[PDB]
Length: 193
Image 1 (cartoon, rainbow, N blue to C red):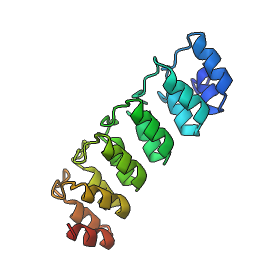
Image 2 (tube, rainbow, N blue to C red; image 1 turned 45 degrees about the vertical axis):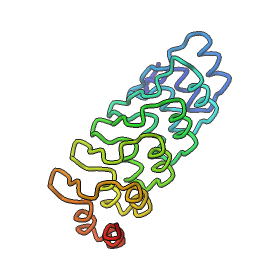
Image 3 (spheres, helix red, strand yellow; image 1 turned 90 degrees about the horizontal axis):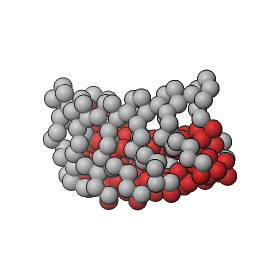
């Protein structure tokens, strides 16, 4: 390790060093070691769009697909926030916990909604993601979609019959938060279901 706390395996991932990764893993290098922010080589691979090391890390049994950063972030959440649909999907197929949440209670679906990542919202829903999940502030993915103006994802959530009546800690509906933020397209949209 060094100054960022990264291991040779972390570096292999950040700089798409495929051969280096295998060699390290074959010598029993720990694939779940945390850097200064708690990221494991898998987080690194996801964060750098390093397809080679990524796949290698997934094929590696010992790898913890639900590894958590110091704020609770998982590779899946990371994948949904960065708009990396291939990785998101491979993680899901390799059985990552679709319903896991970070330190705020946000699942990957919550984040897909916030950043209007329609594609991940569908794959996640297709694979068990709880559509009405509330984070620690009692916000549901749809509430987030409404708040951020994520019309396209909001529609997916609504087409999946997501509950429009679940309010946040301030007892506000997706429709309310979308109104106080001038996302009129969403208000209309909400009134359509």
